[PDB]
Amino acid sequence: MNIFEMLRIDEGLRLKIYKDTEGYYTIGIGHLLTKSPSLNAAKSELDKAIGRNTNGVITKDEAEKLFNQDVDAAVRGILRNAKLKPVYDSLDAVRRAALINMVFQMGETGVAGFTNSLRMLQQKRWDEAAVNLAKSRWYNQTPNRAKRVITVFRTGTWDAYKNL
Ligand SMILES: [Cl-]
Ligand SMILES: [Cl-]
């Protein structure tokens, strides 16, 4: 298992514009297009992202390309963030994947906000960080996905994703 396979499981793959869990226009593998309520604005951001007149539909190759860009950006956002970088550097390879997943979902800003949890992860207090991560809107709104990510932080293994 790896970060790409992990996120492909959590986000799924859709080739036509759809609405995410928050009701925002998205496409591909969890690629947020716009927070705006307008489908046109969404089609416009899609075309600009792909570089062609899409008609709200993309191919698999195009979806994967946005995905690759998005994972790359997630990583870079972590390494440039004063609060995230040190956590990420302190973690083992499996747990780093869990942090990337959170950033991909909620953005760097969002994750950097989990101050207490971050400190606990940095300290390697797994069970305690897991309980603290669960006390969040994130966990209450997307519980199955949050449980998966939290279990990875708790155990350092990919067991939570094996079966899916
Ligand atoms: Cl883009
Ligand atoms: Cl969920």
Image (cartoon, helix red, strand yellow):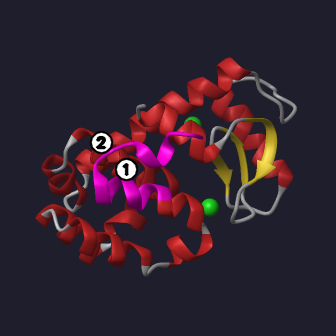
Q: Position of residue 41 (x, y in %)?
A: 78, 51
Dominant SS in magenta: helix
* Residue at left offset 83%, top offset 58%: 38
Provide the residue designation for mark 1: 98
Q: Secondary structure at mark 2?
A: helix
* Residue at left offset 48%, top offset 56%: 148
Provide the residue designation for mark 2: 94
* Residue at left offset 23%, top offset 65%: 126
Name the amino acid type tagged 1. Ala
Question: Looking at the image, which is closer to me, 126 or 5?
Answer: 126
Q: How many marks?
A: 2
| Label pair 2/1, CB-CB below 8 angstroms | yes
**Side (left or right) of 39 relative to 82:** right
Q: Quadrant of residue 31?
A: top right
Question: Looking at the image, which is closer to me, 64 or 117?
Answer: 117
Question: Looking at the image, which is closer to me, 63 or 138?
Answer: 138
**Side (left or right) of 48 relative to 103:** right
**Side (left or right) of 71 relative to 122:** right
Q: Give, as a single range, the part of the protein colored magenta.
A: 148-164
Against 64, residue 49 (above or below) is: below
Name the amino acid type tagged 2. Val
Against 99, residue 31 (above or below) is: above
Q: Quadrant of the N terminus?
A: top left
Q: Position of residue 138 (x, y in %)?
A: 52, 71
